[PDB]
Length: 69
Image 1 (tube, rainbow, N blue to C red):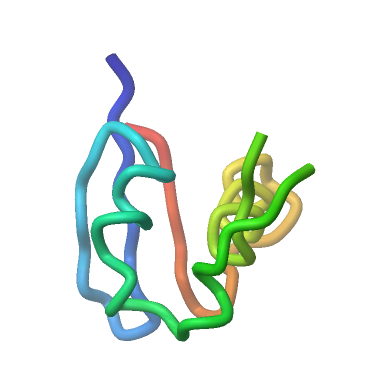
Image 2: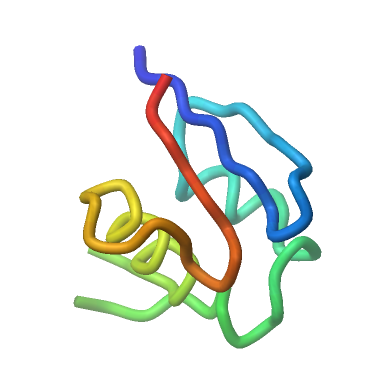
């Protein structure tokens, strides 16, 4: 039962339990190319970047921040 807070490059915040599902339901928040899903399960530029942010490798992906609640 995980919870995540995602902050857009301007401070707007969203809360959800699954990042992939949120991305799939909110394509309009990102550029098109960043939510094209590719195989290597599946990934998109947004999911991979935000997951690297979650791992602590980078504080943000294209201004997007994400943290575990």
